[PDB]
Figure 1 (cartoon, rainbow, N blue to C red):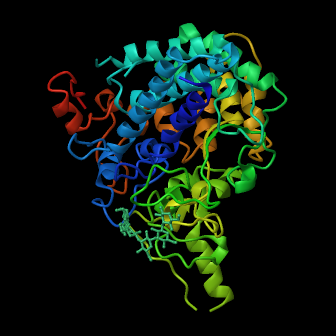
Figure 2 (cartoon, rainbow, N blue to C red; figure 1 turned 90 degrees about the horizontal axis):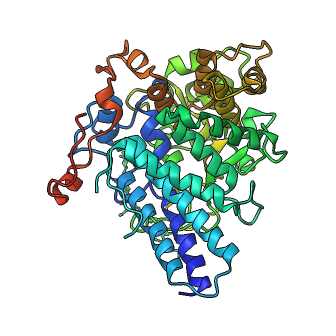
Figure 3 (tube, rainbow, N blue to C red; figure 1 turned 180 degrees about the vertical axis):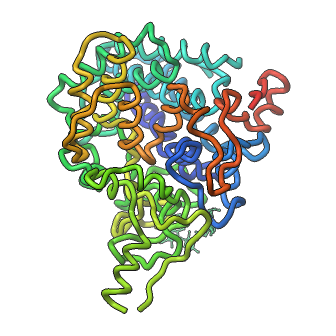
Length: 467
Ligand SMILES: OC[C@H]1O[C@@H](O[C@@H]2[C@@H](O)[C@H](O[C@@H]3[C@@H](O)[C@H](O[C@@H]4[C@@H](O)[C@H](O[C@@H]5[C@@H](O)[C@H](O[C@@H]6[C@@H](O)[C@H](O)O[C@H](CO)[C@H]6O)O[C@H](CO)[C@H]5O)O[C@H](CO)[C@H]4O)O[C@H](CO)[C@H]3O)O[C@H](CO)[C@H]2O)[C@H](O)[C@@H](O)[C@@H]1O
């Protein structure tokens, strides 16, 4: 009813962003949930029954009774908190026009963000704009119409300040617009998407970090390259097993760091050996590409060298699908949970990078090649390519742009969605030579099985996907 209470409610609508990595008794880190269905990582852990839903999804054999349910609950918690704010604003007095617009812009952009999670993973899902199963195509029209309404409020700044980093901005809204327009293959909005990407490119407060290896460091958080991140902190963080929803750190580096690594060696710490980096991922980089070592941390070579320098035979404990490589971007780094005050496992400081300026450039290059209008697709592609330390210029073909995204975004939740929307999934996601993936992707796998408990509780109102 008052301004101060709506302000607190707006803050609460942001909280589900930082939940899925540990919430509702599951690990569903949203970047890995898509990346394990692509061609860059294995699943790992103790065996195929450790986080079993992950191994089933990876092999296109998810089942409604053994599914990732946490992310579903996170997304719909988000939607509910945004809906709360729209309803509260109906019953509010002495809120300025500007503050009313600002509160609406934030919670409607977040609502589309949360719906994007369930739209991409499950497609045909229930919709509510106040506290009905839509087709994927019907949810899309709701989402993109909401984003149009947020842009037209004309209230969001292009970039936030030190104090407010993590708040919705116009650039975040633009990147979210491009993500859903491109996943839908809605070419009637390609022109508008390209105009929005060019507005970010024209801004002098977004640019590439000159060193790719500086992006994923703590000092790289909210750099000139960052459009949107989900904030995680170790500073007096008290996220715990029984209190997963409190704003502290992330579980992600504990999941994907080497099992019984000797903490502090090469300033890396131990984890549970999930998402080992495939050897093929390391091999697809040129020796000149700075992304190779920023993506692929060779844990085994570090100990091989150490055991020749100081011959204590150090080892880590190899788990399932071990390769010797781990995802350096979100690896446990000595000191990145040092200031936490609860369980150190859940309180890593690593922000989750959602949108980076390199995705602005590759979005623009791709929209130009898909007929969105004139622009310098070759300049935009080659800015990303050259930042990686490659000196030879490449043409802005769709295949070169899609492969640049592949090199640029391992572990960032982009590749699986890129493979489906470009029509490459059926050709790329086939049985491997290791006997790990034994199934082939097909269009029926586009949308996961809806969790059985949701099918049951809805008593026929929710129709199961034919996965
Ligand atoms: O498949 C994935 C993977 O799973 C592994 O299993 C996981 C399993 O290890 C985990 O087990 C829990 C375990 O970590 C936990 O241990 C407690 C620890 O949490 C406790 O820490 C306390 C904090 O609780 C406390 O926090 C306080 C905070 O709650 C309060 O609100 O605020 C206070 C400040 O204001 C704050 O203090 O803070 C103190 C420090 O002051 C901490 O010490 O400490 C004890 C050690 O003393 C430790 O034993 O116990 C839990 C009991 O519930 C266990 O559940 O659980 C996961 C989820 O179920 C499992 O995934 C497997 O091992 C791997 O093989 C798999 O690969």
